Image (cartoon, rainbow over all chains, first blue to last red; front, side, top):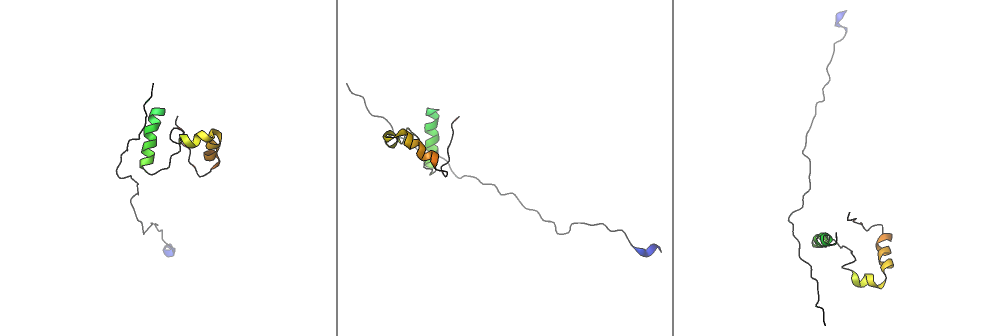
Length: 41
Length: 52
């Protein structure tokens, strides 16, 4: 009775892919601070 | 690190962060140094930057 059953191969059907999300900072700079006062005699 | 720390603090301030450092908050720190330090130590929300 060889027709009893069959072997079956399983696959994951609905696969999906996506891209990674990376953060970045736009622009850069630095304003100078102020300091100092004169000594006296 | 004092000289570099000045540039680092300017960089932080330009990007809108309210940086507390002794050289800049001299007037407030002068009133009571220990109280000034404990102000930022107690507060859990204040991020402390350690300049190694």
